[PDB]
Amino acid sequence: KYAVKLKTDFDNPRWIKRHKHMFDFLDINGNGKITLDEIVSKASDDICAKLEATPEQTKRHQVCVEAFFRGCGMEYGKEIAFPQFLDGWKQLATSELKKWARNEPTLIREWGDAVFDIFDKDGSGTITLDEWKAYGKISGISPSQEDCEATFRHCDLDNSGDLDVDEMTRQHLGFWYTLDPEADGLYGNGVP
Ligand SMILES: Nc1nc2ccc3cc(O)ccc3c2nc1Cc1ccccc1
Ligand code: NA
């Protein structure tokens, strides 16, 4: 009655290969295993150092990356291979889509909040192309300057050509969770 079907396509190779691409990126030494320890050191503490984020921003960012990948079933001290990684993404995505439909806070959005906070010079919550290019290179999500520019042509921008968190979070829902065709090309040619 009150039920609505959630947009998912977890059996599609295009969604599987998206997270396989990122898993290999996390799998620095290419041994097929990753840990939450490495994610939080690389994907958080080391990004915030290069971005010169404040200590509190560094802490808040760590809390959000920590919580996000715990929603994937990862815990400190546990090695994780891709099959488990992808099964956790199925659970994470399904959970996140329900929270979103119910207007409950989502891990993807809070992660986005922590990132935008680092680039919130004036408090209006804007990310400029130049800021994104720096993030994309430091986080490794988008080192190519061309890809970063494609991301901004792809996204809806404000009057200054800038980007806000709601937009990027809605893109992320389509790109990482549901495989919405509207999110295709979010990172240009950097991520399939
Ligand atoms: N910066 C990222 N870092 C990673 C790192 C590993 C990932 C592994 C996945 O399987 C899927 C996505 C990612 C990932 N996605 C982003 C995008 C993002 C940008 C801004 C705020 C929040 C997220
Ligand atoms: Na590894």
Image: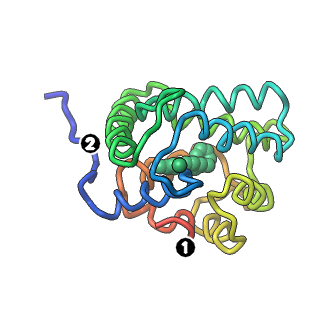
Q: Which mark is residue 6?
A: 2
Q: Looking at the image, which residue is at 68% across and 32% down?
A: 61
Closer to the camera, 98 or 140? 140
- Circle 2 SS class: loop
Confirm or reject: label 1 Cβ below 8 Å from ligand 1: no
Q: How is the image coloured?
A: rainbow
Q: Position of residue 124 (x, y in %)?
A: 77, 40
Which kind of residue does numbered mark 2 sit on? Answer: Leu
Quadrant where the N terminus is found in the figure:
top left
Q: Position of residue 90 (x, y in %)?
A: 32, 41
**Mark 1 residue crowding within 10 angstroms, few (<14) / some (14–19) / many (20+):** some
Residue 164 visible here: yes
Quarter residue 112 falls in? top right
Give left or right: position of 184 versus 145. Answer: left
Which kind of residue does numbered mark 1 sit on? Answer: Asn
Closer to the camera, 179 or 160? 179
Tag 1 residue: 189
Give left or right: position of 51 versus 101. Answer: right
Q: Position of residue 148 (x, y in %)?
A: 67, 66
Q: Residue furthest left?
A: 1
